[PDB]
Length: 370
Ligand code: NA
Ligand code: NA
Image (spheres, rainbow, N blue to C red):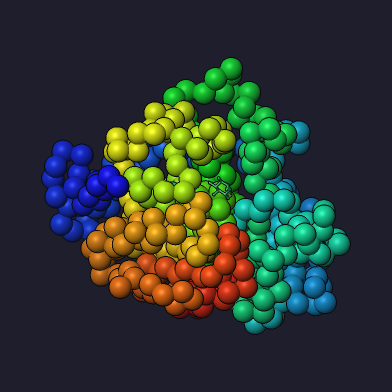
């Protein structure tokens, strides 16, 4: 309903005509703009006392198909420091051929133990529909995951884990207006998980597909935009403040998300409640920050809350940046992916993450990672 800012027009009106101007001038502008006005600033990268502890390693998980590691990523040296728990499945066929496996990495909503029924994972399997682990493994990809609540609660009435506590305490009684919220913390945790993958000799951290569904897809996008080590970015039905254009004011709006989830974004993002016309950015520019690395955005046909048309139109509005790198986006009809390095599909049915979503993502990763 409101015109989108041009990703190729700088803050001073200069037109960006090449990928070198983009990477060196326009990219840092937009990152700062999304930091200040939407997600909050990421206040640290790698902490100096980060410690990796492999707590379990099972060489014959899932009937022999995968090696399974559970890893404590602790962010201080004191063994009582805050930490997150990474679960990693590696396909044993890939290990057997002395290859480092490409990886699908994403946060989960209900706990590492919910991604598969595997009773050794430290409500089991109750989220299996969104996590076809054996099929990903059979296709030759490792699967790495961390529970989002290790880093920050999902609901505003959630319990704090040690990492959320540490950040909560650091925020005193109130956050600064440009301080990060849950999506920024979630994105940061994905980059710390990638830090671990760099050290694990079973996996190729240069071939990591960072994915997320819904709120954790907001986080995957923000992680991929800030951290260009990620090889490929997948946003499944991330909706408002993820891939959907805020200025379309369709489905969930800025005021609605900030009201129900006041810890997800920066306080500054609340200044755009029922004022999306004033946003100096929109989500097509977040998609653009992933270029030239491959980016997959997908919708569900009945998921009006997420604004599927707004998600597709953000992909289209980001395409000119991808075209600076000679990549192509979508030219769509249901169940027909479209686009080259910048890809979109919309499937029938409700909000969710299905076998067909993953079939499309696996084929995408095959093209770019295998
Ligand atoms: Na590695
Ligand atoms: Na919306």
